[PDB]
Image: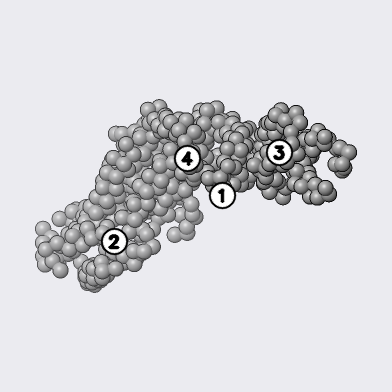
């Protein structure tokens, strides 16, 4: 009858006319060449390189068996033409699966995403369910690795199909699905790995996932405050580095300035002056109060306004990862300025005290002399009042009502950066800082000449009044081009021009 011959070609077994009127051969090739793709699949999807490729390979055999189930089920012996028409709406789909595979071929995520773009490309048509059932199982193992960083945190990779592979401790290199969740997964895992050492709407994935991301991060930040006192370290480093606590800088700087080369630089005096300083603090002497390594960074040789010296805080592991080893370096930048400021309010205090013992001696030469100090002191006691208003109070209002895990890195990087910006240390407003040195220098010369050389000092003060009068113009011209500098005008200029 020949029915059992054509039907035994979709299975792959050869026949009397299938090797490996008269026009029936042409209409036979319409069903024959269908079989050439069925065999061309088992030769390609037989193995049980990549793990996601195996599942997609394991998904194909979940389909062909149905194609083997449909055949040999309905027709015992039907008309010849019935076969060609019955296997048309289904046969052409089998030839479509040849365009998908080879009969090179991506692997890993590159394949799990390539198959996705085949869905939207041919969505409305009848190829939607078959492709979907493949994608629904071709991503099954890939969810498991995603199901590790979310629940357990053990990274299980074999060949690199995962898009992510494996002091600083944050060198798990990272670089389709919605990127709104991609970068979040990368951080939703590193937190767990850090606590261990201490229509195509994708709703079936994010919904069981986003519910767990917010609980981890909230428990991660809460882990820091209520147990490791992150809120304390900030409000403690400010007590020591930014010199917020009086009776400490006025005891440290006051000690060092008593000396001024080979002395004052061995670790016997400068590494001990701190342990004498902390006792006069009336605040501290806690586990926080330690780790104040008063270390130096230069070996100078020999009237100026510079004494290079550093003061570094020290931290331990679960806090080292937040407070960057670069941020503390910038505290050292803002510190050497603030210490340099105290050198004025002590040297200027000296001449105010050095002159006190001189007092009978009342003449025009005397009173006209002392009014210089009153005219120079008021300037420094103004620029200091500015610093003690921006870098310690208002920039601290932010970053204190701002906090209440990635954000902690940026919020801190924004707190200090505003402190060095309002501090006239940025290179943008550098000329405003350069002129300050001319002011500070002249006060030191005024300290050297503690009336044998009055006129030598009278010329010095006149140079001071010129430079100060020059500052009022260079800062004003820098307003048309910084709302931070605005408050300086109201500070330097008041009831004058």
Q: Secondary structure at mark 4?
A: loop
Q: Position of residue 134 (x, y in %)?
A: 62, 37
Q: Which residue is mark 3?
A: 82
Callout 1: 10 Å neighbours few (<14), some, many (20+)?
A: few
Quadrant location of the C terminus in the rendered image:
bottom left
Q: Nearer the viewer, residue 448 or 285?
A: 285
Any part of residue 45 in sight: no
Please report whichever mark, 4 or 2, sits nearer to the chain's N-terminal start. 4
Q: Which residue is mark 2?
A: 482
Does residue 422 appear to the left or right of 361 in the view shown?
A: right
Q: Secondary structure at mark 3?
A: helix
Q: Which residue is mark 1?
A: 121
Quadrant location of the N terminus in the rendered image:
top right
Please report whichever mark, 2 or 3, sits nearer to the chain's N-terminal start. 3
Identified at 40% across, 53% down, the residue is 333
For the residues carrying marks 3 and 4, which lies nearer the camera in this image? 3
For the residues carrying marks 4 and 2, which lies nearer the camera in this image? 4
For the residues carrying marks 3 and 1, which lies nearer the camera in this image? 3
Q: CA distance from mark 4 to mark 2?
A: 47 Å
Does residue 26 appear to the left or right of 478 in the view shown?
A: right
Q: Secondary structure at mark 1?
A: helix
Q: Secondary structure at mark 2?
A: loop
Callout 4: 10 Å neighbours few (<14), some, many (20+)?
A: few
Q: CA distance from mark 3 to mark 1?
A: 33 Å
Q: Which residue is mark 4?
A: 201
* Count of numbered circles in the view: 4
């Amino acid at each position: 009858e020949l029915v059992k011959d054509v039907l035994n070609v979709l299975i792959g077994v050869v026949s009397a006319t299938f090797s490996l009127p008269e026009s029936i051969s042409s209409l036979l090739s319409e069903v024959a060449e269908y079989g050439t793709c069925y065999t061309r699949l088992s030769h390609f999807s037989l193995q049980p390189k990549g793990l996601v490729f195996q599942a997609f390979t394991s998904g194909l055999r979940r389909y062909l068996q149905y194609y083997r189930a449909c055949v040999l089920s309905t027709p015992p012996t039907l008309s010849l033409l019935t076969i060609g028409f019955l296997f048309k709406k289904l046969g052409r789909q089998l030839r479509y699966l040849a365009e998908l595979c080879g009969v090179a071929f991506p692997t890993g995520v590159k394949l799990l995403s390539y198959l996705y773009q085949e869905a939207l490309h041919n969505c409305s048509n009848e190829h939607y369910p078959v492709l979907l059932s493949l994608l629904k199982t071709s991503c099954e193992p890939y969810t498991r690795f995603i199901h590790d960083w979310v629940y357990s945190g053990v990274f299980r990779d074999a060949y690199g199909e995962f898009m992510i592979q494996v002091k600083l401790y944050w060198t798990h290199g990272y670089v389709v699905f919605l990127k709104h969740i991609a970068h979040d997964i990368y951080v939703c895992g590193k937190t767990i790995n850090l606590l261990k050492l201490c229509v195509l709407m994708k709703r079936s994935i994010t919904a069981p996932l986003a519910a767990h991301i917010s609980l981890v991060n909230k428990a991660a930040v809460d882990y820091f405050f209520v147990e490791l006192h992150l809120e304390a370290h900030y409000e403690a480093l400010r007590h020591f580095l930014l010199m917020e606590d009086g009776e400490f800088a006025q005891s440290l700087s006051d000690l060092l300035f008593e000396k001024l080369p080979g002395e004052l630089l061995n670790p016997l005096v400068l590494n001990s002056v701190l342990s004498k300083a902390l006792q006069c603090s009336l605040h501290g002497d806690t586990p926080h109060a330690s780790n104040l390594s008063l270390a130096l960074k230069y070996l100078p040789e020999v009237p100026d306004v510079l004494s290079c010296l550093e003061l570094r805080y020290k931290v331990d592991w679960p806090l080292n990862i937040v407070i960057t080893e670069g941020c503390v370096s910038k505290y050292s930048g803002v510190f050497s300025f603030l210490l340099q400021l105290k050198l004025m309010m002590w040297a200027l205090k000296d001449v105010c005290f050095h002159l006190k013992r001189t007092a009978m001696a009342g003449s025009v030469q005397f009173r006209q002399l002392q009014l210089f100090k009153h005219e120079m002191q008021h300037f420094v006691k103004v620029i200091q009042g500015y610093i003690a208003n921006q870098i310690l109070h208002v920039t601290w209002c932010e970053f204190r009502a701002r906090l209440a895990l990635e954000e902690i890195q940026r919020a801190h990087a924004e707190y200090l950066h505003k402190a060095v910006f309002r501090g006239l240390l940025t290179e943008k407003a550098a000329p405003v800082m350069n002129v300050i040195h001319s002011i500070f220098s002249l006060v030191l010369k005024f300290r050297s000449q503690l009336h044998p050389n009055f006129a030598l000092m009278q010329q010095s003060y006149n140079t001071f009044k010129y430079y100060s009068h020059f500052l009022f113009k260079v800062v004003t011209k820098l307003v048309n081009r910084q709302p931070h500098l605005e408050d300086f005008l109201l500070r330097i200029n008041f009831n004058n021009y």
